[PDB]
């Protein structure tokens, strides 16, 4: 019990408000920013997930396959 820290994964700080959940994690409404552009999202947006990064629906399209992936098995 008792309050302390149990929410965000980037900063590891509880989140009172909404949390950006992508796949199986949770982050703050500011901590998690599209790696491509880095524009905050809403409290329930839909985007493509890869490994552990947040890729926008329009952004990803561009960063689909650009010198990314050393080993392709
Ligand atoms: Zn955070
Ligand atoms: Zn973006």
Image (cartoon, rainbow, N blue to C red):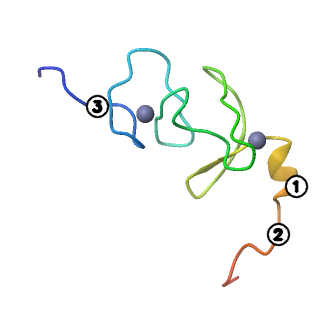
In the rendered image, the quadrant that contains the C terminus is bottom right
Q: Disc 3 vs disc 1: Cβ atoms closer than 8 Å?
A: no
Tell me if I can see residue 69 in this picture: yes
| Element type at mark 3 | loop
Q: Is the residue marked 2 within 8 Å of ligand 2, measured from its CB?
A: no
- Quadrant for residue 51, please give it: bottom right
Instruction: Specify the label residue 33 is tagged with.
Output: none
Residue 48 appears left or right of 17: right
- Mark 2 is surrounded, within 10 Å at the Cα level, by few (under 14), some (14 to 19) or many (20 or more) other residues, namely few
In the rendered image, the quadrant that contains the N terminus is top left
Q: Disc count in the image? A: 3
Residue 26 appears left or right of 4: right
- Mark 3 and mark 2: Cα distance apart in space: 36 Å
Q: Disc 3 vs disc 2: Cβ atoms closer than 8 Å?
A: no
| Element type at mark 2 | loop
Q: Disc 1 vs disc 2: Cβ atoms closer than 8 Å?
A: yes
Residue 44: x and y in percent read 63, 23
Report ligand 2 position as a quadrant: top right
Residue 57: x and y in percent read 81, 40
Give the camera-side residue of 50 and 37: 37
* Residue drawn at 70 percent across, 82 percent down: 72
User: Badge 3 is on which residue?
Assistant: 6
Residue 27: x and y in percent read 47, 34
User: Badge 1 is on which residue?
Assistant: 62
Tell me if I can see residue 73 in this picture: no
* Residue drawn at 33 percent across, 31 percent down: 13
| Element type at mark 1 | helix
Residue 39 appears left or right of 20: right
- Mark 1 is surrounded, within 10 Å at the Cα level, by few (under 14), some (14 to 19) or many (20 or more) other residues, namely few
User: Badge 2 is on which residue?
Assistant: 66
Say above or below: 17 vs 69: above
């Amino acid at each position: 019990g008792s309050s302390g820290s149990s929410g965000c994964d980037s900063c590891e700080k509880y989140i009172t408000g909404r949390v950006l959940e992508a796949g199986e994690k949770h982050y703050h409404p500011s901590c998690a920013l599209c790696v491509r552009c880095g524009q905050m999202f809403a409290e329930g947006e839909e985007m493509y997930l890869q490994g552990s990064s947040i890729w926008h629906p329009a952004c990803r399209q561009a960063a689909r396959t650009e010198d990314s992936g050393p080993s392709s098995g």
